[PDB]
Image (tube, helix red, strand yellow):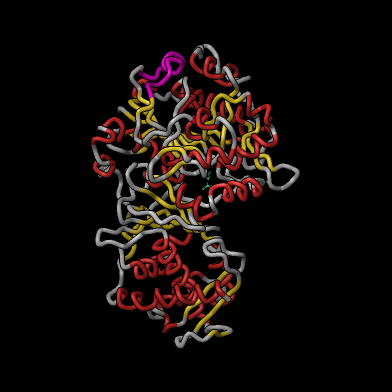
Amino acid sequence: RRCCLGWDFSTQQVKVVAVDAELNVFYEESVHFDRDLPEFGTQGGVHVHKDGLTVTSPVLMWVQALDIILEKMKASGFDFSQVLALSGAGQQHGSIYWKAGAQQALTSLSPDLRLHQQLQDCFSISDCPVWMDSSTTAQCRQLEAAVGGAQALSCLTGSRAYERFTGNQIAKIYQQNPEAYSHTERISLVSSFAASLFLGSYSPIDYSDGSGMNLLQIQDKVWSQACLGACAPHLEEKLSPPVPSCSVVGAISSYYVQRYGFPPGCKVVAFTGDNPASLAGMRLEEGDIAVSLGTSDTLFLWLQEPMPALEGHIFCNPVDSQHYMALLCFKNGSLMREKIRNESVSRSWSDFSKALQSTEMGNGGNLGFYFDVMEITPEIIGRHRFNTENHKVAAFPGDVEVRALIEGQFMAKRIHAEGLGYRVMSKTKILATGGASHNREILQVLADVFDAPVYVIDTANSACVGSAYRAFHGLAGGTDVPFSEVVKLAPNPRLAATPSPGASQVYEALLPQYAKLEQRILSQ
Ligand SMILES: O=C(CO)[C@@H](O)[C@H](O)CF
């Protein structure tokens, strides 16, 4: 049983899966930060600072967690001699600042000691900013002004300036702690930091996670000189050139060979971000989209031809370096669905389903926008309801309300995805995951709106699994072969719904009416 390992250096834990060559997951293990390393005093794996905006994690907690998990695997009897290759994912945006002289410690690791003990003094910043940090608003505004505005930055990097994006965090560290910045020889993302631990030398950053920094020119796949210069000095030499995601960055360090019994030929495939790795785990191809339903709803799009905007995030594609992917986040998700269920259908998901069954596609032309909290895609708040003559109304009947919510939420996902360059194709598959993916009637509206089949998939280990798939892709030929042909044998998702007859005719007319009403609300 030969295998690849798929790692996930996440906010709350370090996780690993072992996938065999038939692409079956046969082993999983994890180390949970608060529970297993309580000495760091984290909550949710992070430290929220007094200001309520600065959010960090101690770098050495992530190092120590890797030591614990490898020893936990050993103690369970995991056969490391069977590992042909490995890759992994990192929580996006988060950064590691390596102190001058740290690569000498990485390259001289002794198998008799743990990583934590040997890399103890290798970091110029002990508390790493993570994806939850929102303390860099001034750096965001300065970065945008320096390059010609929010739209100019997005065209260049796939996103306007976001507080959590790495370049804004590097700028804040350079401004507030210039001494630590001057003593930093290398800056890694969580993904490339974790790859560096397995190599025993610095890994480059990949194109895909490299796209979550407001630094990489996504088109030319080179660092933007204007973005680098607007954040901190000598930054390019600290980052090193970025590489295609399907790159063998080196063999595993002899440290792991001697300490754990990994074979010396075990290959380390470039790590990537957790969202890009989940896209690989979900096996999205051209024309596909995944809908992650939850407290926030997240759209994962494949993009051949990107159109960066003031909303969403375009990244270089992890499984096809010539194309792209995008994330679109919706703040009004499951709480909004639960509130409408409670108000209109007697707190019953069954009556919620029956309201969708008992109403026609297009809802008689009744359209609704439901934003009890300020929405981000787009920036609107309030509930806004319109009847078949496009007149604003105060309320709908209960059943109409349920369909207006579900049908509007899915039409918005389609409209905002097309704003970034996405187009439904004859090959299109829609993948759905999360709480609301357990409701057939909700998934039917989704199938009708996009005029494409919907499949349900469990994604709890999507980043791990996607990483093991990418490791297998590197062994099966890398850039010489399509990722999709390597993973064709992986488990297929179950088909949940297919568009009803006439759905295309209904939504071809209704989608432009919904988009016009959205623009009407934004302007007024
Ligand atoms: O900030 C995010 C995406 O831009 C998150 O999904 C982090 O990757 C979670 F770790």
Q: Quadrant of the N terminus?
A: top left
Q: Nearer the viewer, residue 391 or 233?
A: 233
- Residue 499 in sight here: yes
Q: Residue at x 46, y 62 (%)?
A: 436
Q: Is residue 192 magenta?
A: no
- Say left or right for 401 vs 128: left
- Say left or right for 403 vs 170: left
Q: Residue at x 48, y 73 (%)?
A: 352
Total marks placed: 0
- Residue 11 in sight here: no
Q: Residue at x 72, y 48 (%)?
A: 52
From what the image shows, is residue 397 above or below residue 268?
A: below
Q: Is residue 258 magenta?
A: yes
Rendered image quadrant of residue 353: bottom left
Q: Position of residue 224 (x, y in %)?
A: 47, 40
Q: Residue at x 45, y 27 (%)?
A: 203
Q: Position of residue 477 (x, y in %)?
A: 25, 32
Q: Position of residue 179 (x, y in %)?
A: 68, 27
Which residues, given as a range, are shown in magenta?
A: 250-263
Q: Quadrant of the C terminus?
A: bottom right
From what the image shows, is residue 271 above or below residue 289?
A: above
From what the image shows, is residue 234 above or below residue 117?
A: below
Q: Position of residue 500 (x, y in %)?
A: 30, 73
